[PDB]
Image 1 (cartoon, rainbow over the protein chains, first blue to last red):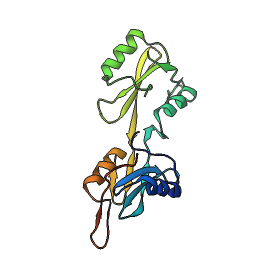
Image 2 (image 1 turned 45 degrees about the horizontal axis):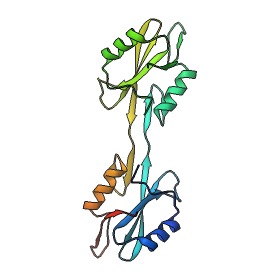
Image 3 (image 1 turned 90 degrees about the horizontal axis):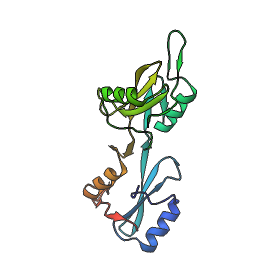
Image 4 (image 1 turned 135 degrees about the horizontal axis):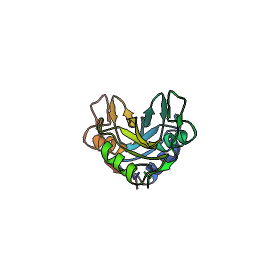
Length: 98
Length: 98
């Protein structure tokens, strides 16, 4: 993800912008105040500004369950059944078709 | 994303499972019936079963706008202002801090 600078703090973002930033230069970093979100830190008018960007990450929903990644979904259904028949027959995922 | 097989149709998934699939083998493909979602196609009990997986993709929210990717967010704010002061001074993103 080329658009992401680094997990630098608000203060560290300012230090970088003060050292080598110019009008309109920006960086995108993890938010300190809200660790799962981001901040866009911008040099403008001789000052540094910070804008919060809230992330609602991906949700994979199947039946009544929700997973943040497809890998998690897959593993879950190797240990718990993805379908139980009415005869109680539990069907599980075993491995990917090559 | 190693977990994704391909944009094969329901019928093509069955053909692959019939040709070389065994009990518990599965593949994850785009859904035909709902193109932005997925389907898990599983061989179990000599039969092929298909399970819908709904995707709510990532949302990046900043102010009053929502974007599906950070790249889109960035481009948008190079053409429209990310902040307008009360003097009407429009601040835009220009480029990434190296």
